[PDB]
Length: 118
Image 1 (tube, rainbow, N blue to C red):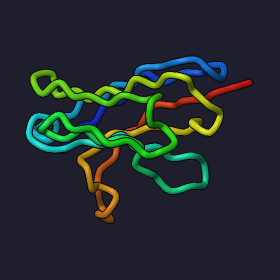
Image 2 (cartoon, helix red, strand yellow):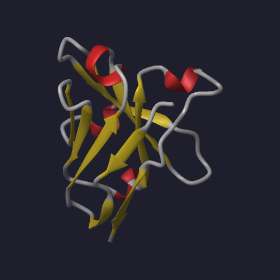
Image 3 (cartoon, rainbow, N blue to C red):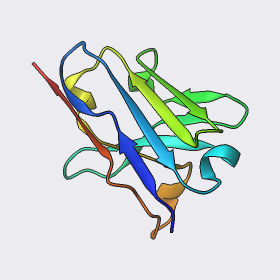
Image 4 (cartoon, helix red, strand yellow):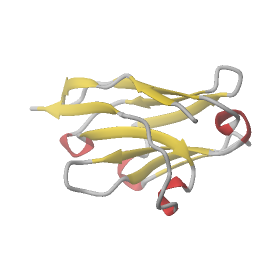
C-alpha cells in the first residue's frame, strides 16, 4: 500500500502564504512526475502544478507567479510554496503521480486544508 502524507495547510488572510508538503512512499516521487491538485467542496479535483523529473514545472494560469512546486527525490517529498493567496485558492490540496485523476481507482491521501479569508 502507498502512503501519501500531506501537510502545510492553514487559514490565512488574502495575500498571505503557506508551504505545502507531501511525502509519498515507494518510487513515485523519485522516478516520476508529480502534481499538486486541489478540490473545493462539491467540485472535482483539478491539477494546479506539476514537477517533472527534468526539473521542468508547469502551473495552471491562475497560480502562475504565485505558487512554486519542487520535489526532493531523496526525501520523497513534493513541495508547493503558495504566495499571494487568494480566496479562490480555498480548497483541500493533494499530491499524486501526474495523471492520477485519469484512474478511477487512484489512491489519494487525506490532503491538507487551505482557507483564505478576508
